[PDB]
Length: 207
Length: 211
Image (cartoon, rainbow over all chains, first blue to last red):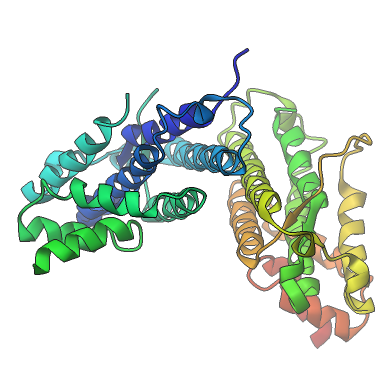
């Protein structure tokens, strides 16, 4: 029975985002809430790239030696419990909701600028990453996932000597986005979740 | 085990393994009472609903919407405590021995220590018999971890109380909990500490100190 490791759990955490839909009560806020999730996911995938998660055998063992890797193992476990909690919360709502409320947005409900950005952010992570849909029905559950994953990645970044590397990665994620309207959107949406992306974008808009 | 009563009794028992770390400072006593009150309010619910006697709560695959709802809520309270312990463990792994020292109820004033013991006793009296099996004791090392538990448990017990017809029953129960506490000092403390977490206890204390 071959036990769990940091890379495996980490790949799981990234994949949890793929399955999330946003319910009708997001309303006009759908577009930016979806981008906040994409950014939370961008930031998590960046950490893996920065620590070279797929090459370093330390993230592939059941019983890691380093405190740092042991810390990462716990954090990634805790991200998974976060998504498991949200999944239960969604299921309790679906148990009780009428049909009109069990409706979700799709990215075609985003303006062309947010949708291009949504797809860029999603492609960016699938480029790095060598179950069943479910919905977030209220803003509070989404903010919990965004804020807590930001917090978790804060401490994932703290445990490793990778800050210069994370800033470099964030700067080259943004090289493909050239237009001021889009750079502005990322600057806004990376607000309080991905300071490295926000700063990379702010730098571009004003130079 | 995995019926609602078994998961519920596990939730109440989660509170017993929790220590508060050095960094609570002079807020130790109040934060500990806030935890005991959340535990008292969760256990009040099990009593109100007759959790240990009602067979709906003893099946692994309940059909009733309200009982399916309680099972999810109780599983989510469990996840809540599982998360806090991973957070605590991450602190332990990196801290110095100075920072690993925990408060004990001897660090409360006699008034708070009596409330702590009374609130604990009241739940002990209600809980289903348990074996002697222990989980590892673990500490909350920051204020925000404590607030996260207290606040989320209060919201979860709001959800639990919403799914069952027990409004008047919970009020009577909180009145009975508070009948042995005679002194205005201790009652003001419960009135205040129950604020935001247990309105039934808050109101019961208020009704008693005004009488």
